[PDB]
Image 1 (cartoon, rainbow, N blue to C red):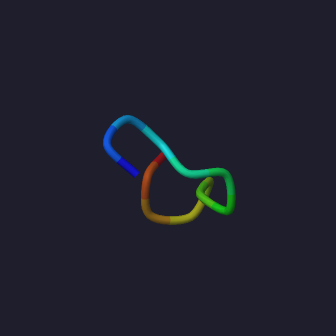
Image 2 (image 1 turned 180 degrees about the horizontal axis):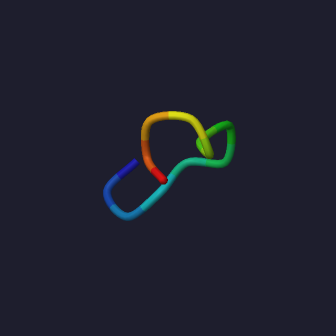
Image 3 (image 1 turned 120 degrees about the vertical axis):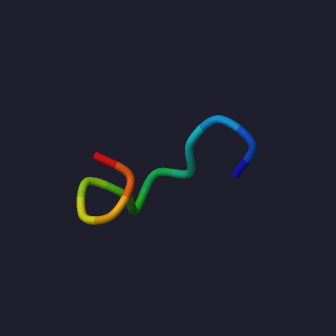
Length: 13
């Protein structure tokens, strides 16, 4: 959450 979750690659990337 602080750096990156896992389910990202949608909003994070």
